[PDB]
Every structure is written in C-alpha cells, then in structure tokens.
Amino acid sequence: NETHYAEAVIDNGAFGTRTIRFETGRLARQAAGSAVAYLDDDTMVLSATTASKNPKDQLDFFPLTVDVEERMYAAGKIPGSFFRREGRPSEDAILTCRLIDRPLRPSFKKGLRNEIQVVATIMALNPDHLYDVVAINAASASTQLAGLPFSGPIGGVRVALIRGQWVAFPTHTELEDAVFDMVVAGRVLEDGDVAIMMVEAEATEKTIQLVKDGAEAPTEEVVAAGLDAAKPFIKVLCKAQADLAAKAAKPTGEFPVFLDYQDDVLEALSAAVRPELSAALTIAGKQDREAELDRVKALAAEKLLPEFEGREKEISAAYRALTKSLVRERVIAEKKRIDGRGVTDIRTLAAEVEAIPRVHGSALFERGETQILGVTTLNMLRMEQQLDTLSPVTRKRYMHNYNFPPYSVGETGRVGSPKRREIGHGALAERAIVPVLPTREEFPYAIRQVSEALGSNGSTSMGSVCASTMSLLNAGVPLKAPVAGIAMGLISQEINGETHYVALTDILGAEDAFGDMDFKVAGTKEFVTALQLDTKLDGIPASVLAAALKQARDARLHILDVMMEAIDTPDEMSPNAPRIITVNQIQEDTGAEIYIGAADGPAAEAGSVVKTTFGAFVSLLDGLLHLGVGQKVQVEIAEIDSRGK
Amino acid sequence: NETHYAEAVIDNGAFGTRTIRFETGRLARQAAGSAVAYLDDDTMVLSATTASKNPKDQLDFFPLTVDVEERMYAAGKIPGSFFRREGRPSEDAILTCRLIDRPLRPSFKKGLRNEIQVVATIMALNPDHLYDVVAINAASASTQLAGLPFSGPIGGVRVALIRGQWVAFPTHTELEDAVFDMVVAGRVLEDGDVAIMMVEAEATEKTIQLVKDGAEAPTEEVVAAGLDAAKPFIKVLCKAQADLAAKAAKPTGEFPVFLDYQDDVLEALSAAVRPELSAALTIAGKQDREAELDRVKALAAEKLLPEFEGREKEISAAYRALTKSLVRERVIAEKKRIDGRGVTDIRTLAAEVEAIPRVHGSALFERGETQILGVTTLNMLRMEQQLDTLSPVTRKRYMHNYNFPPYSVGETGRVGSPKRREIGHGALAERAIVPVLPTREEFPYAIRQVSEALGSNGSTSMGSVCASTMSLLNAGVPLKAPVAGIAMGLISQEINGETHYVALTDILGAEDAFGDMDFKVAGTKEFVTALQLDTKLDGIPASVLAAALKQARDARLHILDVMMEAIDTPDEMSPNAPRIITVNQIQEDTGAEIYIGAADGPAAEAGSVVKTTFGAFVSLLDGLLHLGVGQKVQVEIAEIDSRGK
Amino acid sequence: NETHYAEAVIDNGAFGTRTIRFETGRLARQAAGSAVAYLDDDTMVLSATTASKNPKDQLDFFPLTVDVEERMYAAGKIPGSFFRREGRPSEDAILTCRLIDRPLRPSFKKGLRNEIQVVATIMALNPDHLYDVVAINAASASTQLAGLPFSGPIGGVRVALIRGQWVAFPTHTELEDAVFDMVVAGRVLEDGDVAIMMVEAEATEKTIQLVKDGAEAPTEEVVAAGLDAAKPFIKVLCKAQADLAAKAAKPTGEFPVFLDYQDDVLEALSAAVRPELSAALTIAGKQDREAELDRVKALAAEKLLPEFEGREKEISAAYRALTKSLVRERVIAEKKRIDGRGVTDIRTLAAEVEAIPRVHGSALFERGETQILGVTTLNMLRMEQQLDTLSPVTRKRYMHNYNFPPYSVGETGRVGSPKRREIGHGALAERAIVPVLPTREEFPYAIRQVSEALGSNGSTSMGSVCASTMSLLNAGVPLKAPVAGIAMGLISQEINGETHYVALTDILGAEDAFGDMDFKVAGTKEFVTALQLDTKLDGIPASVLAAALKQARDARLHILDVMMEAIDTPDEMSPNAPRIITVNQIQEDTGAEIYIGAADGPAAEAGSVVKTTFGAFVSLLDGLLHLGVGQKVQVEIAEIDSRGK
C-alpha cells in the first residue's frame, strides 16, 4: 500500500514547460485500477477503472462504459442548478467520454464481454487549463493498472498551431492566437514509433483573422505537420504511464473470450457460397445486388442446415467476415467498390435551399442515401444559450442540434434525448462551421441550426456541414466562406510482404466497417475547419496520409461547387426574422428593446448595415456607400442627391 | 424515386377555402412509409412510419407507438429551455399522439404483434393554424403507404361552429367566435359513406357570451349536426390520401398473426362451463357473482386439464370471449347488465364538499367504485403556468392535474410522471370546465385543480368533472354554471339480418371492453361542454345516436341534481386564500404587491366586488348594491345611511 | 362499507395536548389496506398499501416500496415548478420514505417475495406541523389493515428536548427552543413493553446557544432519557392503530415463502467444511484469511457436488448462515472479531487536509477500507439553495452532497442520480454538522460540502462527518467545535436461558449484517449532534444501551484527537474564495455587489471581522482588538498608534 508517481515533461519552448503528473496508490484503492493526473500540479483528474466479474456473453459487442464527472467545486463554484448539485452531463463531459472511448475501446482484446467502466472525475481546474486531454491520460493510466487485457498506455495530447508553433496542452490564453486546435491520441509501438489512433481537430474562431494578419492557413500540409508534432508528446505521455504501470500495475487477469463463430462454420459457409457471394458482390445495382446477395444467404443458410442447428448466429457472423474479406480484396486488386464506384467517386449529390416553409432558412442535402435537412432560426442575442459548467464559456451564440430519428434507417425506436453520437456528430458539424461565422458585432443574432438526419447511410455529420452552410446562407447569415465536408476511408492489406493502401472517397456505412481507417474532413476552399480520424493501423506512410487528405480535399472542392449552384451569396434576411438596426413609452408599445432591436421586421422600420449588392445601406436617423447584415461602421455624409440620397 | 402529390380542397364558403396538400417521395425515403401534409402550403407536418422486422409475440397487445415532435423552428423560435433544445413533450404533443393513436390503432389487423411506430414532426407552423389535425392526416397518409395490414386512409378534421357555420380547419382567428370546437376522424366505407371513428370536442371560453349575444347553444342536436358536417371533409381528406396511395403505396406485406386462443380451447371451455357461466352472470350481487364467477373458472381450469397443458393463457383468453358473448347477448335480449342494472340506471352516487382540511376547496365524488377527490388551490395570477410551445397560448390560468395511483385499482406500480392517459383524461375534464369559469377580470386568481383517482372502475375523467365543479364552488370560484359528466356505452349486434342497438348509461369498465362504442359527455344544464367518442362501427342510425346523446343528457341532469344537494352557490373564499381588493414602504412590510393584491386575507384588509347574497360589497377606500368574488364595476355613491353606509 | 376511527391522545402538559386520529373505510377502498392519519384534525396524510398477486421469486430480497407524495395544495400553494405540477421528490419526501421503510421492512415475515407498496400522500399541512411522523403512523396503519404477514402496528413519534421536557410531536414553533430533535419508532411487545426499533435524531442549530443560556447539553445520558420518554407515546400510537385494526383489518392472507436454502444443504455444507471455516475465521490477516476463506468455499463447493446440482445458490446462502453463526459465536465467547480486533478497537485511522488543489477546502479521512474525500466550496449567499416544498424552509445555507460511485467497492454501475441511501447518509452527516456552524451574520457565505466515498467498507456517513469537519476548518469556516462520528454494532445471543450482549466499536460492513443492532453516533466533545439506530431486539437493558453509547463516545473522542492533529483551528480563507468586508459605477466595474461583497479577494480589498490569532481585524474605512471570519461587531476607536494603528 504505497503511493507511486511519474511525470511527462511537456516542453513548449518559448511558451514554457508544463507537466502531466500521474499518481496512484493513494485514492480509490478498491477499483481494479486507479490513477490521478495533474496538469502542473494544479488541474486534477481522478480516474477509476473497474471490471464486472461476470461477462455479459449475451452481448455481441464489448461493453465499455466511460463516464466524466465534472465537480463544480473544481472551479470553486456551487452548482447554479435549482438543486445546487451537478446533474445531467455538460457537452464537454460527453465529448470527453467520446475522446477517451474512441482510442480505449479498440485497445482491449477482441471477444471481451466483461463490463469495463472508466470514471474520470474533474476535482480541480485552473480556469486557464482544458481538462479533456488531462482526462484521456488519466483514463488510460487507471485502465493500464487494472490488470485487464488492454494494450496501453494511450497518450492523449492537444496541439494547437499558435504563431507557427504546435503547442502541446495549450491554455485558453494561448489558444487566443490559435489557427487550428487538434486533439490526438495514440500508442507507442514495440519499435518506439508512435502510432496515432484518434484525431479530433478544428480550425478556430480566430483562424481567418490571424491568417489575414499573417499566420499560415491550416491546409492539409499544415494539418499533417501538426500530426507529426503531436507524436513526441504522445511518446512522453506513454512513457510516463508505462513507468507508473511498471511500478504498480496489477498482473493481467485471465478473462473469457467470446468468438463470433468457430472455424467449422466459416469453412462450411465459405465452401458453400464463396463463389456466388464473390459474384453477387460484382452487381453495381442496388436492388439487384441485394437480391442476389439474398439468394446467396439462402443457398448458405439452407446448405449448412440442419448440420449447423443452433449456430445460426455464427453463420451470419461468418457471412460478414467472408463478405468483408471479399469486398476489401476487390478494392485492392480491382479498385472497384461494393456499389460499383471508383475509389474517388462521390455518390449522387443533390443540394437545395428553401426546402421548408416559414423557417428563417433551410436546406436539403442528399448524397446517396444520406439526406440531411438543415433549418436555421435567428433570434435576439438574449436567446443565446447560457452555460454554467467547468468551461470558461458562459454563452453560446451559435447552437447546432443534430437529430437522428429511428426511421432515418427504417427502424422503430426511442425518439427523445440525444445519444452520445448525436452529440458527437452535432459537435463536429458545429465546430466545422464556427470558423466562418460573422462576429456578434457584425451579426447581433443568436443562431440555432438544426440538422435532421431524415435519411442515413453515408456520414451524416459531414452531410450536416454542407446542409448548415446552405441553410445559413439561405437565412441571410453573412458567412465568411462556405464549408463542405467529406467522409473518407482507407483499406490496407499486405500482398506478400508488401503493404498496399487504397483511399476511398465518400465511403458508405459498409466501407467504414470494412476499412482500416475512417477520417472526415470539412473546410472552406482555403483551409480545413474540422477533421476527425480513427484507426488501429501501426502508422501509415506520410506519402499515403497526404495523398488521402489531398483526395479528400478534391472531393470537398467538388461538393463546394455543387453547393454553390444551390446558393452563392446570402439571401435576404427573412421578413419573419428580427433586426437590430442602429439609430418604456414605445419600448413596450411598438414592441422592441429600444440602438433599436425588434423581434420582427415591421417594428424598428415601420450606423449599422441594414442591407449589403451595389453598396451598404447603413442606418442613420439610412445611407448608401457604393459590413454584414448587421455590422457596424462609422458613417459620414459625403453628398446629398437631388432627391436627397 | 419520384415525388407524388394530392390535394384535399376544404371549402368554407364565406370563410374562404384552404387546402391540405399531401406529398411523398421526397423526404425520409428509408421509412416504410412517408408523407408530408401541408395546410395551405404554409404549415407543414412530416410523418414517417416504420415497422420492426421481428414481431413481439411476447406481448398480448398490438404495439403501436405514435410520437409528435414539435420543432420550435417551425415558429421561428429558439427553444427557451435552459439547454435551448426542445425536450419533454408539451401537452399538445401528447394530446395529438392520442388523437392519432385512437383511430389508427384499431385500424390494423388483429393479432398484429410487430412494433409499428409513427413519428409526426411539425416543421413549419403559421401562427394562425392548429397543427393537430394536419398531423392526424399526415400520420394516416405515411402509414397507408407503409405496406402494412392497415385499413386506411383515416381522415381527420376539426369543425368549429362559428356564427352558425361548421367551419373545417378553423384558424385561431376564426375560433374567437366558436361556440363549439370538435375534432373528428373517420374512414370511407366501400359504399362511399363516411364512418366516424373518433371524436374529441369541447365548448369554448367564448360559448356563454356568444350565446348570450345571439348564437345557438351547443346542445345534443347541434353537436350531432356538427358530426354530419364533418363527414364531407373526412371523405375529401380520405380521397386525397387514397389518390396518393394509388400512386405510391407499397404493396401490403405478409405479417405473422398471433391469435389469443385456438378453436379447440373455446369449444372445450364452452362445453365445459357455458351453463354455469351464463348462470353466474345473472347474480346481481358483487361478491356473490365474483364468487360463483370463480367456481366456474375453477370448474373450467380443472376440466380442461391436463388435456390443455401449457395453453392456460388461451383458456383464460377464451374465457373472456365467452363471457363477453354472454354479457352482450343478455343486454340485447334481457336488457339486464352484468351488475344487475337497467340500460339507463346510474350507479350509487355520493357527492360531498369540505372533504380535506385547510385546502382552499375540495370535494369527493363517488359513483360505484369510482371515487374522485378534487382539490382546489387559488393563488396570485403570477402563479399561472407559463408556456413556450408551438401553441399561441403563453399562460394558463386554469390548471388541471389528474392522478391515477396504482392502488386506485388495488395494484402496486410506479408513482411519478403522469401517463399519456393521465394527460388525456386530465385534459378532457379540464376542457369540460373551462367554458364556465369566470374571466381574469371577474376572478383575478390562478386556479389549480387536482383530481385524485383514489378509486377506479367507472370513467374517472367524467367523475373528475363532477368533482371539479363542486371543489371549485367549495373554494369560492364563481362558476357561471355547474358541469357534470357521464360515460356511455353502446352494444350492437344483428339478430338475423337485423341490427339492434342498446345504449348503456354510466358504463362499468367491463361494459367498455364488451361494447361497440364508448362516448363521454359533460356539460351544464343548458349545453355540452365536452364530448369524447370512439367506435369501429360502420356508422349508426341518426335516430340511435340522438337517442344515445339524449339518454346521456338525462343522466347528466340527474347527476347535476345530486351535485346541487352537496353545494349550489359558491362558498365564501377561504380565509387561507389570497384576495385582490381594489382601492416598497409597506409593499414589503404589510406583504402584498400594492389596486391591492394580498397572498392572505389579513393583509389588504387589516371598485372590486369584495363579497357578493343580498347585493355586492364593492371595495372603495366598501359599498353595497342591493359581479363575482373579484369582478370589477364602476362605483357611484347613491345614499349615505345614518350609520354612514 | 363503514368508516372507522381511533385516537392517540398526546399529552404534552404545559405545551398542550394534541391528537393523532386514524381513519379508514372512507377513502381508497380498492387498496389492500387504507388509512388516514390526522394531527389535530388539521394535518392529513393518506396511506394506501397494496400487494401484487404474484411473488417475485426471482429476487433474493423482500421487495418493499414506500412512496411519499407531497401535494402542494396541502399548503394552499400552486407548485412553483415550470410545469406547475409537483415532480421529483423533495429531500423530506425521500427521508420520510426511509423513516417508514426502516421499521416496516423487517416487520414482514422472512421469505416474503410479493411486492408490497405503501404510498403516503400529504393532503393537508398546518404550516406549524411536521408531517414526517404523522406519515410513519399512517403507513403502519394502512399496512396493518392490509391482511399481510406484517407484525405491526408500528408507532412513530418525534420527541424534542424543549426546555427540559421531551415534547411529543413538537411544532416548528416549539422546536425553536429544542436542544435535540429525535424521531423514534417501535412496536408493543406481547407483554406491554415497548420495543424501540428505529431512531433518527440530531442536535439543532439552537443547541449551543440554549445550553449557553442554561439548558442541558444533549449527552448520552440525556439522549438515552429521551428514548425512554418516547416509549409511552409509541404505546399510545400503537394501541390506537390496534383499535382500528380490531375494527376493520382484513384477515391475514396465505402468502408463499421462499427460503434461502433447505436443511439438507446446510447439514451437508456444515459437515463438509465447518472445521476449516471456523479455523479460517481465526486468521487476523486480510489476504491470508480471504485466501483460506476461499480454499474452504472450494472444499465445500466441491464436496457437495454433484450431489447438489442446481442448488448452488442454496450452498453459498447456507455458507453465509454458517459463517454468521461462527463469527457471532466467537464474539460472545472469545470476544475477537472477524478481522482480529477487540470489541472496542478502531480501525487504522488517517486524517489529512489540503488533499485537493485549488478547492476552497478539502480533507481526506480513512478508517480501514473506508476512505472519504470531503471538499468545501464557499460562495455568496445568493448561491444558497432555494426550496419550495411542504417544508417551511425556503433557503438552505449549508448544503451537503454524498457521492458513492460504483468503484468505491470495485464495481461497475450507473453513475448519476443519487440513490435513496446517498440521500439518507448525506442527510445524517449534514445534520451532524449543522449544530456547530457559524450563523449567517457571523459567516455570510453559502457553504457547499461534498463527500466522495472513494473507498467503502465501514460506515461512510460517519466517516463523512469527520471529513466534513476537517474540510470545513481547512476552508476557514469558524466552526464552534469539531464533530466526529462512529459506527457501532451489537451482538446478542442467549447462552442457556441467559442473554449476553457485546457492543462493537467501528463495525465493518460484515459485522453490520451479522449484528443485532447497528447505531451511529456523531457529536462534539461535549454532546451528541446526531444518532441513527436500527434493531429488531425486544428492548435491551438500560445498563447495556448506556454502556454502548459510552463506548461509542470514547471512540468518538479518540477520533477527535486524531482529527485535531490534522487541523485544530480554521485555516486562512482561501484567496480563491469571496469576502464580504463591511465598510453601478464601480459595482459593475470593480465587480462586486457593493457593505461590500466580492466574489474574490482582490476585489473589496485592492465593522466586520476581516481576520481573527492575537485579536480581531475588523473592517472600518481596518482595526485590531487584542467574532468569526465575517462576523459583525460595533467598533470604537480606543487609541491611535504612532504609525496610526
């Protein structure tokens, strides 16, 4: 019963040095594994990992559960909730579970059915620090000590490109000059190289201005450079955890493994339908393929019976392994996809605005079976969301909600509270847009964007980005630039001692499951505003990654053109929306928080840019100059026309 | 993959023409069935219907699920909730699910066990339109296209009697002159006649004044006339949906059916106990009947064993079919009920006020095993509920809550959030009362009424109406008139090519299950304030319906007498309640938002009617005139008595 | 169908007489059992008890469910919640369920598996009365009439020591002079003596001052005296219920009993391992014992197979009965505990402050495997919780939250809303502290205390008390005195016609399960601030109880010493905390509700005691007098030093 420590020294040169200190042996001694992670001995996150004794063999998936508990006392604050007790998880808490779960899930031995829970509690937070990345490491650390079939440690780091330097674990203060904010997690291979496993990045609300003022825009080259910059830190973080584990990790336990199917089922099934299956997979038609792809299942589920009775699940599971094998192989050799597309072909696109009546703005975006409806709502800033969490953010001007109803995929199910993925995809698409939004002063409105995943089969979050851009422009939001997104995939298998890679454009839901890496990129025509990535591959050639990002860029540009046809410049602000033209009695009669702010056009009406094609009509007592849909600008009278203009 | 449309033209003559446009093929293509319904191309409701592949054979009831999703952007509003995202369903959403579920549920083939879900989303709403009825049609439309064993289309319409005309799909503007608001849904029979299936109606807060000013009160004759007025519209709505289905409906699928019992069980059971059963059912006594009615189950469940082992459920299920058959038959032939009452006899009534201590007002209403406790609470108007939904209503002065605890029926179970039926019954009883409440000015208090279903077996919502009237009067609420309700039933079977009908007064919970129609009527001595109805019958003779309504009226009048004995005129306003007598320093000392508004009697005290038997004591600096318990009236001094009166 | 009554006359002499009236037969006639309990015909509580027909044989515990429903109309109030409808249970409601459940649960026959639910509804409440104890009796009454294998009635009473007299059912008015508030519940034995079964007591926020002004401090002697004072009342309450049951109780039904194991399993298991088990239990070492204690289970679970196949559960259940038998026996004879401690030995203690960075105050308390982390947060009074329940309390200055995460015991599980025990333990530890807190005026801050049960195995609520004291002092809260708690146990078995008792100090979780009584005591060095007790014993010798309380006192004093070493006097108030030094323009610039109230130290700074070692630095325009960390005191200048002091 002794306390052990280890440190990961983070050297940011001119920006200073900071340390991630790991501790174990003092707190929560009843957990399978426990560790504390401090950022400069100031911010503290405790992580406890536990495992249920009995496996849930009933499930066909590894049951991992990650929970992030924000304790408001870590900020010296008493919860503002009515009951003065922290309750339902904030966005940050949920997004952090995702950041931890993504790289930790695939790190456990396959077939594991025991419930593994990881609880990270934020106990102290310096208001200038970001706890998410401190928590990733603490999560990995406690799990690594738990004596479970887990291949860690996993090192997590945030690198932001601040003034030309990729700073590790930047502070909120340092992020004010960041053109790109990127979280990365990975492991250290037996040969010392770092394998990146997870990436969640974004451009910022500062990017455009900073690039204007001289900084380098976050293009694919820059972003890829950032990924390399994160590796040394991840190695340092991993080495520190390994030193802790070396001193106090429990010995790996003996856990039951649950296979999806035995060999006799696969050999049987393979021998029974392999030919018909590999053939059916060559049908470039939807209903035709699925049809023959059905005859086969039949010829199989009928040829293996009654020999294999009560093993039906193994049959369909083996049917999946075989299909996957066949589909992957065809991509590497024939470079043809399960739907007949080439490795860089995008699915049938359809963009459109004015899809719903009355709403301030709306757009419909379809790509294959993915159909997203985006709807925009503009209100007074008083409607902006108010937050009281561990984040320094207290108000949110741009709000995105992503709904994924069951019938989106022809299913029945609960319709209500948003899942963790609905929060995850919603965030990415929200973050992909934020970089191009006008400022509070240029556009004094709270903006709520809702993406309805009416149809789903091909990256709805990315489709959501395209729908947001158009919907917003349709509503009159003076975006600095349109943003589009694309979901990519990567197949990789070694053909006789040689590894080949094939990057896939706009991957189907199936190609995600059969791929070795899936990454999503969104951005304007100039730079990347968002990037998400996941993979278990032991690193990939720089030439390959860069090639994948470039391919993704191309797709993104093509889409931006299609979107451009739908709408280019912002449309006029809906009459049904509010205006804040600058120029009790009538404040409660004319209806408007009189600088005038009306909740309807027929108010303030019957200097601030009241309208900006051949100039800018700035409000006065308005004027015209041969600003946005609400921007501010010092006005001076140059000439009074005959009519009095 | 093409978009199809159809239109139902609603002609309201002088009030104008409007259209319900149906669309399909553009949105939510992954759902079994999908359709959009627009009201004048302005208000839009999307409906997606899906079916789970696997039947839930475990259940003994068809698992239908209807969800209504109000999107605040349909109103150009950002949710006011703390999280700025619509969450827990508003009353309207829930009540709308009920309106859709009621006529759609019985339209599916019996024995269906597949989960069928219908999700209606309100995407755009003209603030002058009511979306509920647009949603009923959209729900029916998407389901009709889903390729399910569903006998639609179902047409839903709201007809309100405005200035002598039954206007279809009235607007909030047009409803200001409505004396009756009635929703009706039905189907079109093979012969072209419309079969009404569901009715949810109510008198309004305008009725009394409008009738005063000349309009015709909504009596049974008027109401029945409205029902006929809804038929042509329902035919138009059905024809439009049928035209859509004709163009794009999927072909009916082959679904598994799950019988409650096989013939061998019924023949066996019938042969085994039919005589004893038909005899036991003649026992007019409660415990006696249930006793012999138990000997029989035994003689049965003992005579069919061990022959029928493992089919026990079929036995009791068949035991139900047989009992139902016997009970129904006896009503038609003998006109005697399972409890010994005649077709028009009301159960033992008991009314009483002052049932609970301290509360501002209370009443206890018993009818057979139905026992309702109503409790009244009066507070300042600041306590009136504030709403921010798709409804134009923003504040609710009269609030009704209906609780149905498990022990109400001798059961254990969850005690917490109110079920959809608790909301449904609560609404009806709330709507049955609203028409007779005094106005804000006549009575400046927020009124909360709670009905506790302490005992249940005979229409608790109607019993709730009677309990509300008395409780309110007990509290001093100057109701314009007392309201009473009654639950009716209708048995109908054809005796050799000839159909007979028998209307039942104050039906027991059992007679509801064995009946062919169940309708509830509530109202004052002069008119109907509420009506609810459900049936699968292919329409009934006008003479029969009118007869049923008249019978119901009679019962209602009898009850009003019994209630009158309990209390006639309002009682004095509880001292423990607030007063708003009209006549910082002492505003925060004497305690009262000083026009004076006290939260207790000992405030404002130690022109507005301060008390009104031989006149009206209007506040002054009070006076007496040889108004309600708070009404306003211009006061003038006529004579100063010797004592100074 | 007749209404029956009974009365329990509560005679408080000079304080008056009150009555608890029981009623049955009028309301909720469908429940298995129903009764109303009125306090002076003013406060009313209705209780309905029901039983599910089918036993839940799957469960290994009696499924009792108690629900308390606060109806705001009982207070003539409309719920202030947004939906104007009472929702999630208040603290009082939950704590009341606990008070009712604790004595009612063990009163049912063992092996009972039918779901028994008790719903108590507060329908009317005199604002000067406390409904909790009225509800305990109503709960017992309705259950006693339900015809269940229940050994009631259970009488519940609150006795508070007011001016030297133990007043039964004191009012909020009378409690203003109470030095101790104690709830007690018990039953009447066949011989007429009262057996106390449950106790939930606390000192008050008035204690210290009242003792200062002359009253007698609530020491173990005083407290024990109170327990005797509650007996006559409990007998009166029981007799009244018995009179009601005599008149209307249903006859006891025939319910299925589910044994944990049959005799053949115990005889088999006993014969198979008794020797090795009794021996393994002599191992004073943790891992060593549990190890041998494992060999035994094996030698057993291997010697009874395959003879006992499919009865494994009975084996482990019998293994428990045997272990319990052995452990209890050893305590009585050898006076040695399953962990090797003597009957009065405390587990290894460890106290420490400054355990977490940044937080205003924190402390870590360990006792054996029990590890509690307490964290303190100080904010402006505006952050104090606001309540709108049936309690007269409307604001709460001191808030305690107790978290018990799953990994606290090496388990996985839900992490979110607090269980009823988390509320129960949190309350006790909250109530144990309240008596020593400074007043609003002496300390103008809202105080939130959070106890994290990071490790659990030995009364975490009591460990929570010790952690609170230290954490609070660490934060600078001028407590009047430090408070410590201890969990005790009592083993009692009669050795040949003679009953022996053995009181256990700081019992392990196991000794609680094997004991016959478990009570927790907390308090300062001078008196008891909290006491909790539970037992089924037919009363115990006064000499024994007093001995147990004295032993507990000793332990408590020892702990207070250990805590004293960690911290004695309050530490300086964290700079990161707010100050309210007494001395729009700068009110919104300097940041502080200007009497000055800053949310940070660098505000008000760059008469009220600004700091109080050699005197008290009271704010002025400050001064020094050779008060607390915010107290108020009239300041006068006596002498101006050369430097100007």
Image (spheres, coloured by chain):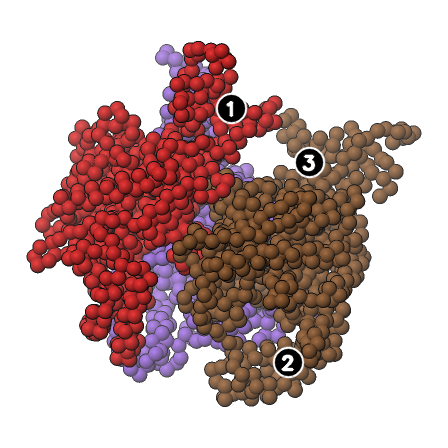
Chain colours: A purple, B red, C brown
| C527 or A611, nearer to the observer | C527
Measured from the top left, where is residue C633 in percent x and y?
A: 79, 34
Q: Residue A259 carries which label?
A: none
- Residue A164 left/right relative to C252: right
At 76% from the left and 72% from the top, the residue drawn is C342
| C322 or B118, nearer to the observer | C322
At 61% from the left and 80% from the top, the residue drawn is C322
- Residue C410 left/right relative to B528: right
Measured from the top left, where is residue A352 in percent x and y?
A: 31, 43
Q: Which amino acid does label 2 sit on?
A: Leu
Q: Kindly state the secondary structure of the residue where label 1 is placed.
A: loop
Few, some or many residues within 10 Å of mark 3 (<14, 14–19, 20+):
many
Circles 1 and 3: CB distance less than 8 Å? Answer: no
Where is C475 relative to C58, above or below? above
| C29 or C182, nearer to the observer | C29
The answer for which chain carries disc 3 is C
Q: On the image, numbered disc 1 is attached to which residue?
A: B596
Few, some or many residues within 10 Å of mark 2 (<14, 14–19, 20+):
some
The answer for which chain carries disc 2 is C
Q: In which image quadrant can residue C270 be found?
A: bottom right
Q: On the image, numbered disc 2 is attached to which residue?
A: C293
Q: Residue C598 carries which label?
A: 3
- Both marks 1 and 2 on one chain: no
Measured from the top left, where is residue C291 in percent x and y?
A: 65, 80
Q: Which amino acid does label 1 sit on?
A: Ile
In the rendered image, the quadrant that contains the C terminus of chain A is top left
At 23% from the left and 41% from the top, the residue drawn is B554
Q: Kindly state the secondary structure of the residue where label 2 is placed.
A: helix
Where is C309 relative to C623, above or below? below
